[PDB]
Amino acid sequence: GSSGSSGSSAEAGGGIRKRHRTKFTAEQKERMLALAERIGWRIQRQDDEVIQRFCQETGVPRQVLKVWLHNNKHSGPSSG
Image (cartoon, rainbow, N blue to C red; front, side, top):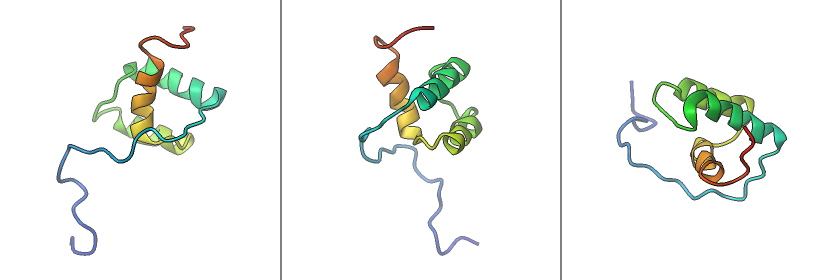
C-alpha cells in the first residue's frame, strides 16, 4: 500500500512543540511515578508499548512523559 499517508517511520530526530501547560494530578503524577519507577524514569523502544499504552490510560503525551521524568527527577518533589 502506502500512498495516502506518508511512511510513519522515516526519521528519528523529532521535536513537536515544548512541554505545554500541563496539569498532572495525583493520578497522572503517581501514574508516571509508578511508570518511571517501572521503566526507570527512562524511555526505550521496548517500553514503547507501555509508554504509548500508558498514554491511553492517562492521556499524557510521550514527549511529556519524557521531559516530565526530567521535570520531576533530578531535584524536585521526591518522596519514594
